[PDB]
Amino acid sequence: SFSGYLKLTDNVYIKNADIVEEAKKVKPTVVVNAANVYLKHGGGVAGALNKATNNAMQVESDDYIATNGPLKVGGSCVLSGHNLAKHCLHVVGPNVNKGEDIQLLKSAYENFNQHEVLLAPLLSAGIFGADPIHSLRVCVDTVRTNVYLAVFDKNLYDKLVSSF
């Protein structure tokens, strides 16, 4: 199961780890992707997870979008986890760089409550432009299921832990 995590609360755990490497090691039931509404997995966590699937995540996602249209900001969909997990929960946090309402971050985290345990990144962090300290606080105050957060950047991980 999950190893090396620091316990933040009853249900939230955190580790300085590459979520792709973490997923390959653990093969969790659910890995969360930091998705956009078009499921275009170009960069950040999405680009890295998709590259690890040899683009199979993108091919599956394009078919999903062709059938269903785009997701909502704050919404999600469950697709295959490919070689990374049983399932991938594609969750769209607001992208502050695209001018999206930061209050949609709580709605985005609410999607995690439909899964008993998840491996996840901090939503709206990284290239999505939100403050990761704020994302962690919203995560802790919204998610009630067991969430194992992988924070790629060591300096950010230390700042998140030391300021919690």
Image: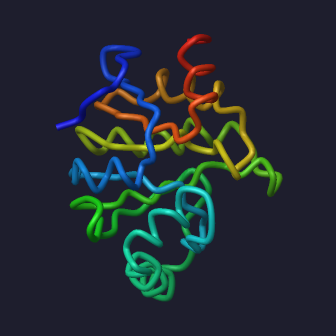
Q: Quadrant of the C terminus?
A: top right
Q: Quadrant of residue 2?
A: top left
Residue 5 lies, in percent from the top left, at: 33, 25
Please tell me which residue is depicted at 43% across the width and 87% down the height of the picture: 63
Left of 149 or right of it: where is 160? right
Image: 149 above or below 70: above
**Which quadrant of the structure image shows residue 71?**
bottom right
Tell me where residue 31 appears, x and y as whole percent.
Answer: 34, 52
State which quarter of the image contains the N terminus: top left
Residue 143 picture quarter = top left
Q: Is residue 42 left or right of residue 82?
A: right
Q: Give coordinates of residue 66: x percent, y percent.
A: 50, 88
Report the label total. Answer: 0
Residue name at image x 54 percent, y 39 percent: 122
**x 64%, y 42%: residue:** 125
Residue at 27% in and 44% down: 115
Q: In this rendering, is residue 149 above or below 54? A: above
